[PDB]
Image (cartoon, grey):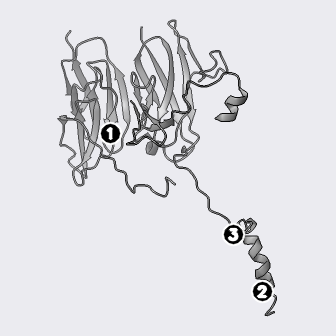
Amino acid sequence: DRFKIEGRAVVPGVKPQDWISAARVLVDGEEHVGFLKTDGSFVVHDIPSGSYVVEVVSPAYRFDPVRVDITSKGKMRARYVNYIKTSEVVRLPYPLQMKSSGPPSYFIKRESWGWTDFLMNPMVMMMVLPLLIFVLLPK
Amino acid sequence: VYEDQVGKFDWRQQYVGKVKFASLEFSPGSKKLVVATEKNVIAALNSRTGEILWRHVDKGTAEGAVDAMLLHGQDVITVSNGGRIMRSWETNIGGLNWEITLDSGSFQALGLVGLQESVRYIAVLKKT
Amino acid sequence: AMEATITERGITSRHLLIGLPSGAILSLPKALLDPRRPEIPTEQSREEN
C-alpha cells in the first residue's frame, strides 16, 4: 500500500521561479526526497504508512516543518511539530500551505558606541568639566 | 562579524559525479550543457565559463538511478529508479515541468513516437 | 556526520561539530551536554557553574 502527498508553498514576494532554483523538500531527511514544480508544489509518491515531518530545505528563505500522520485507511492528519508533547495541539486542513517568514539570520550583529552615549563614561565626564572651564576663559 | 568577513579565508569547490548521459543539443546553445551523473545528481554546466547553473540530488543509497534520458527542443525528459517515477525538467530555468508514476515493471527501453507532424507521445516498453 | 575539535595542547573548549541533511554544519559546546546536570536546582550546583 502506497500513498502520495502534495503541497503548495507560497513566497510572500519575489518570484516563484526565482525561489524554485535550488529548492527541495525532505520527508525524513535522506529517505524520501521531493522536488518542487515551476511555481511551487511538492508531490511525493512511493511512501509507506507512518508519521513524517515535511520540511522545505533552502539556503534562502526558510520554512517551518509540519508533522503529517498517514493512516492505512487513507486519512491524512497534519499537526504542529511537537517533541516534548505527543498529543494533538491544533488541526489544520490537509493542503499544505507553508508561508516562509523570511531570510534566517546567519550572521551576528556588532554595534559600535554612540557619540551621545560615550559621554556617560566615568573618565569622559571628568574631562568635560576642565573642557568647559577652559572654554569659558577666552570667551 | 561574519557579514563583514564574507570570504576572507574560506572556499568551497563544487563537483559532480562521472558523466553517464550527457547531451550536446540546443541549436541556440548560449551556454547550456546538461549532464546526468551516476550519483543521482543532474547538473548543468556552462560551455563558455564552466560553472554550475542548476543541479539536483535526490538519492544515492540504492535507488533513484537514471536509466534513460531523452531531449526535446527545450524540455528534457528522464526516468529515475527503475520504472516507477518519471519527471521532466527544463533548461531555460531549473525545476519540474511535470511528473508521472509508472506501474510495477522492469524498464527496458523508451522512445519518441510522432503522430504525423511531430512528437506527441513517448513510448515506454517494460518486461511485459 | 559528527566530529570533535581537537587542539594540540587542549586548553580551549571542546566543541562538537554536527552535520545536517540540509548542509549547514552546527557546532555546539560540550558543556551543555554534561552528565552533571541536576534535576532540581541545587544551591551549590547553581552557585558554581
User: Which chain is home to disc 2?
Assistant: A
Q: Is residue B37 above or below residue B110?
A: below
Q: Nearer the viewer, mark 1 or mark 3?
A: 3
The quarter holding residue B91 reads top left
Q: Which mark is residue C30?
A: none
Looking at the image, do the residues carrying marks 2 and 3 touch, with CB atoms under 8 Å apart?
no
Looking at the image, do the residues carrying marks 1 and 3 touch, with CB atoms under 8 Å apart?
no
Few, some or many C-alpha atoms within 10 Å of disc 2 (few <14, some 14-19, many ≥20)?
few
User: Which chain is home to disc 3?
Assistant: A
What is the C-alpha distance between the residues marked 1 and 2?
70 Å
Q: Amino acid at mark 3?
A: Trp
Left or right: residue B3 compared with residue A134: left
Left or right: residue B6 compared with residue A128: left
Q: Earlier in the sequence, mark 2 or mark 3?
A: 3
Q: Is residue A60 visible?
A: yes
User: Which chain is home to disc 1?
Assistant: B
Q: Amino acid at mark 1?
A: Arg
**Looking at the picture, how far across and down is residue A41, in whole percent?**
47, 31
**Looking at the picture, how far across and down is residue B82, in whole percent?**
26, 18
From the image, tell me which residue sits under label 1: B55
Q: Is residue C29 above or below residue A106?
A: above
Left or right: residue C30 compared with residue B41: right
Q: Is residue A45 above or below residue B70?
A: above
From the image, tell me which residue sits under label 2: A134
What is the C-alpha distance between the residues marked 1 and 3?
50 Å
From the image, tell me which residue sits under label 3: A115
Few, some or many C-alpha atoms within 10 Å of disc 1 (few <14, some 14-19, many ≥20)?
some
The quarter holding residue A44 reads top left
